[PDB]
Structure formats: C-alpha cells, structure tokens
Image (cartoon, rainbow, N blue to C red):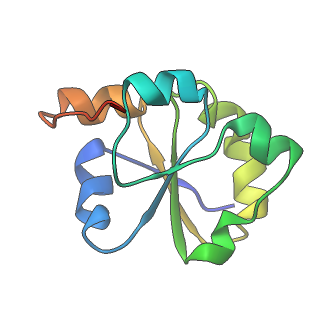
Amino acid sequence: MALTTISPHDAQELIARGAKLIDIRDADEYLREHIPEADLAPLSVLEQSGLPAKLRHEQIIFHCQAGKRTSNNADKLAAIAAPAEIFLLEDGIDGWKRAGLPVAVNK
C-alpha cells in the first residue's frame, strides 16, 4: 500500500541496483519485444496462481504493454507485495522505448 509511480528513467537506475522488473501481459507481445532484464509472468498467471515475487527480493516493479494490465493488477500486487517498496512504470515499456532506449525481440 505504498506503490509510487516512476519514469522509465528511474526504473533504469534501479536495473543497475538489482531491482526486479516484472511483466504481466501476453508473452505474444513480450516476444516481439522483450527487455533482457525483467521477469515475464502473464498477469493471469499471478492473478490465478499468485506468486509472491516479493519474496524473490525487496523491490519489485511491474510494467504492462500500455499500463493496462498493471492498473488492474496494481491493486493485486500492493497486497501481495506487502508494504514493501514497489514502483510503477508510467505507460509501461512504450516509455522505456521512447526514453531513447533500444528494445530486444526474441529471436
């Protein structure tokens, strides 16, 4: 219950720290475009399975194709992520791309 929004520019500074980036959408979209530095877990996988990814670290971030799935699970995470320290990727990956950073497609 302390999730704060961040800019693709901040999430990066963390990628260097160890932050745990997680994606909750359709791999089909993650395949054509993926960022070799984040975990892939289809929302439906967490909403139905419920994997306390928070236990695999202290800080966790979630990003959706276009901040569509995150806004839906955003409430489901804050709960499973306890009062820990979670951030929010404004827009999602669409930003990291425009931010002036290249993407990686699954060959």
Residue 44, picture quadrant: top right
Residue 7, picture quadrant: top left
Q: Above or below — where is 38 with respect to 45?
A: below
Q: Position of residue 104 (x, y in %)?
A: 27, 35
Q: Above or below — where is 61 with respect to 7?
A: below
Residue 4 showing in the rendered view: yes
Q: Residue furthest left?
A: 100
Q: Quadrant of the N terminus?
A: bottom right
| 8 vs 52, nearest the viewer | 52
Question: Image point 42% across, 33% down: which residue?
Answer: 92
Q: Quadrant of the C terminus?
A: top left
**Apparent side of residue 104 relative to residue 28 in the rendered image (left or right):** left
Q: Above or below — where is 82 with respect to 48?
A: below
**Apparent side of residue 74 relative to residue 8 in the rendered image (left or right):** right
Question: Image point 71% across, 53% down: which residue?
Answer: 77
Residue 66 showing in the rendered view: no
Q: Position of residue 50 (x, y in %)?
A: 82, 54
Q: Above or below — where is 41 with respect to 2?
A: above
Residue 13, picture quadrant: bottom left
Q: Position of residue 40 (x, y in %)?
A: 55, 46
Question: Image point 77% across, 47% down: which residue?
Answer: 46
| 101 vs 26, nearest the viewer | 26
The tally of labels here is 0
Question: Image point 39% across, 22% down: which residue?
Answer: 32
